[PDB]
Length: 147
Length: 147
Image (cartoon, rainbow over all chains, first blue to last red; front, side, top):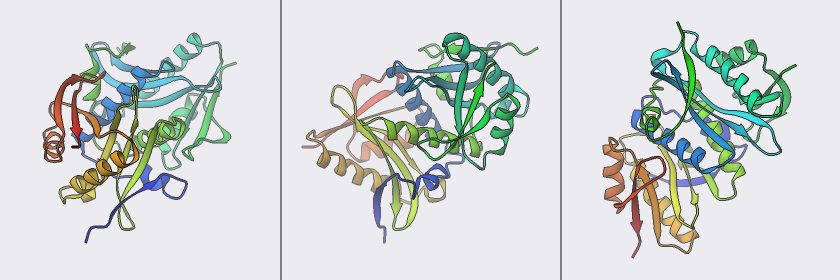
C-alpha cells in the first residue's frame, strides 16, 4: 500500500529533491512563482523584478544582498516562448550592471547545479567564474569580480 | 530592436509574472528548487521536506510559522510521474496533522491563484475554506480550523 512519510532535507536527499520532475505542471508553477513573490515582498533584503522587452514580459529575476553583505542573483528565468534568442544574456548583463551600480561592492555571486551546462556557459561568457565554494544547497558557487 | 528593462513587481504586473511560461524548462526548475532549499535552510522559521512513498521521493513541501504566528503551507508539489493517483491528498492530509501536532495552533493557512481549480478542490475536500483575506501576492487565502 501507500507508505507516505516526510524527510528533512539533507545532503542525502537534497539533489533528489532538486531533481523532482515537475514538467508540464503549469498551475503548480503559478503557485511556485506566487510564493517567490510573497517571500521577496516581505524580506527587506530581497527583490523581485519582471524582465521586459518593451511592453512584453519575457522573464523574471530575484536578487539582493545576503549575509555577510554578498550580493546574489538568486532566481533568473526567461519565458519559454522567448528562449534561444539572446534575451538571457542581454538581461543578465544589464542586471549585473544595475547591481554593482546599486551596491558599493564590485562582486556578484550565484550558484549552479552541475548538469546545467547552458547556464554555466552563459554565466562564464558574462565573466562569472567558479570560486571553489559550495553553497548551502550543495551547488557550486560562481563569482563575478568587476575590475 | 531589443528594449530590455526591469520593473518592480506590483499589483500591475504581479499576475503576469505569476503566469510566466516556463514549461519544459527542466534545468531551470532544478535551479528554482535549489534556491527554495537555500532559503528554507537559512530561515529558522521555514522548513523543507521531501515527500516519500516508501523509498521513492514523490514530492516536496515547504511550511512553517510566519508573523504574527500563523502557520502556512508555503510550497507543495507532487512529482509529475506520480500525479493523479491520490498522493497529493494523502500527503497533504498527513502534513496538516503533523503541523497542528508541532505547533500550539489549530489553524493552518495557504493561498491559491484563482485559475487553480484542482488545488482549490483538493484543499476544500481536506477542510480548507476561503477566509476573505488576500495575501501580499494578491492570492486568495484559505484557512483550515481544526475543532
